Amino acid sequence: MAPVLGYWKIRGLAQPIRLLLEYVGDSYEEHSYGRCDGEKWQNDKHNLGLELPNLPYYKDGNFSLTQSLAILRYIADKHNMIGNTPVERAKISMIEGGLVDLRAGVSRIAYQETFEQLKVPYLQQLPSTLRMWSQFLGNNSYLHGSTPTHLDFMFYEALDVIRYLDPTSVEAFPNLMQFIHRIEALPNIKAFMESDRFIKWPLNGWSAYFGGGDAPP
Amino acid sequence: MAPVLGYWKIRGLAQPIRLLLEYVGDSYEEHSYGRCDGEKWQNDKHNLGLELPNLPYYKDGNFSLTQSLAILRYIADKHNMIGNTPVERAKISMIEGGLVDLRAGVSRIAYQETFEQLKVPYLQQLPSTLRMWSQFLGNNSYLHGSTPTHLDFMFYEALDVIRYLDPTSVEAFPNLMQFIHRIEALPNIKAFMESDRFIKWPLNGWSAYFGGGDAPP
Ligand SMILES: N[C@@H](CCC(=O)N[C@@H](CS)C(=O)NCC(=O)O)C(=O)O
Ligand SMILES: N[C@@H](CCC(=O)N[C@@H](CS)C(=O)NCC(=O)O)C(=O)O
Ligand SMILES: [Zn+2]
Ligand SMILES: [Zn+2]
Image (cartoon, rainbow over all chains, first blue to last red; front, top):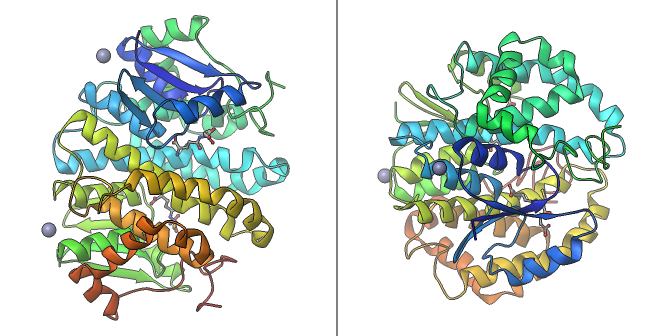
């Protein structure tokens, strides 16, 4: 019995954790809740023993966790990706926070029925947001240090979702386009994404007006 | 030139940082932006050399940070409050993310015109969330370990903001009320709350329909 990752059968908040685990090659099992599996989650949520029940959850025998960033960080920490001194640990936590915000900017408007109109000031403001990430990355291959960390898988998934929302926005920054292909070329990431384990869709929860439904529109 | 904390002159995301800095008694300068000090922020932002510009920011010498949780954790890390093992560190990250959600539940709805109608489902769901937190605190004085951490100040603030929105919701859980009085009695915190540094209002941005404007309604 490997460590279990529990989440909706969507990319959402779990995709970076899935990408990280496949990158480092660790053993894990997913317990995936499909669109009609709400009751089953209601049962686990009551019975699993989670101290702060939520999705996603992570459970390895008696040890359990909720909160996407806590679970990412637990795996990142087992691999020495959360930095070495108070200054570095803090820098890494900043970058995390910004990447949380970058993904959630999509999430915040994607469930709204007025998505198509919220999209317009979203795209007016996005170039300055992408510019800041594009300048922060500069000509480094990765966000922090010289090898892939959890930060890169957060950043990847946010850039891939935004590129699907509006490709021209992301194409204005050559280094963010090259980052995207660099991650998809990491051999473990490429093998994952070619496997039947990979959830390509939906981006958000099924009920979203952008990146929802069972299949791309 | 002690450490600068920069933020709008609101409680919002920085209040727990102020309460923590106060609690450990470390020296710090606040640069506050008032409701029409927005142009000022843009100019400062221009010069602060922030890698990922935002508010709140924290700056000490040539070390700068954004993201509220990363600032909180840097201060907490310098005081041994982020945990001393991988399981522990992770657990603390999970509680933080929970507390981020707890406070953001109010912000999500507070800016909308339709706040008063969003409020109805919110308070339908609120007792089982408060119940989750009440059981997790259980008999302890503090959320994690036996002395106060950044966690407690995040929790205190979120509880106070919810107390305001609906006093009857929080009064149902005696251990949570006691928690609030405990935090309030802490000598450095009492002194802080009696000083004219202390920001009691607004809870959120001035433009919010709840916990906004110039004064309690
Ligand atoms: N801040 C949390 C958000 C988790 C959350 O909101 N989960 C949603 C799906 S994205 C959910 O279905 N939670 C379980 C529930 O509502 O019972 C995190 O990062 O894990
Ligand atoms: N997740 C971020 C959110 C920061 C944020 O949105 N800050 C707002 C105020 S609460 C802001 O005014 N940012 C300044 C700017 O965008 O220039 C954090 O926790 O610090
Ligand atoms: Zn590993
Ligand atoms: Zn100190």
